[PDB]
Image (cartoon, helix red, strand yellow):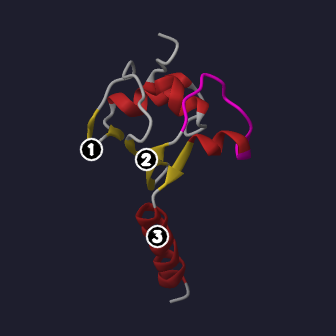
Amino acid sequence: PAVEVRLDKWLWAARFYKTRALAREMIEGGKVHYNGQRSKPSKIVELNATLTLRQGNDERTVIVKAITEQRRPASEAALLYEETAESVEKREKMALARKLNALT
């Protein structure tokens, strides 16, 4: 089955975490959810799955659009998923509010 890529490898390939070991720690900390639930490092990624993950102190919800074992460049990896519009908005709004409480 050459259509089986682990969630920890995937998260690293997609550049969400610097190393697979870190991606594995985040998963085990419950900081990454797969279709709304705790997952595991060895979970095989499926196209269109919904992943919710912690980025520093940001939360992003992305939909898996491609699977690969290669970690490509910044702009290139970024193409293995599509962040949801609701996720981008939530992030923005929190960022804005941050900059607001700042100018006050």
Span of residues in magenta? 66-75
Image-quadrant location for residue 80: top right
At label 2, which amino acid type do we have? Answer: Arg
For marks 1 and 3, give the CA distance: 19 Å
Please tell me whether mark 1 or mark 2 is closer to you in this view: 1
Mark 2 vs mark 3: which is more N-terminal? 2
* 34 left or right, relative to 84: left
Q: Magenta region, mostly helix, strand or loop?
A: loop
Which residue corresponds to mark 1? 36
At label 3, which amino acid type do we have? Answer: Glu
Q: In the displayed image of the protein, which residue is found farthest to the left?
A: 37
For marks 1 and 2, give the CA distance: 13 Å
> Marks 2 and 1: in contact by CB < 8 Å?
no
For marks 2 and 3, give the CA distance: 16 Å
Q: Nearer the viewer, residue 65 or 6?
A: 65
Give the answer, above or below, for where 91 lies relative to 39.
below
Q: Which disc is residue 89 wearing?
A: 3
x, y percent for residue 23? 48, 30
Which residue corresponds to mark 2? 54
Q: Nearer the viewer, residue 10 or 64?
A: 64
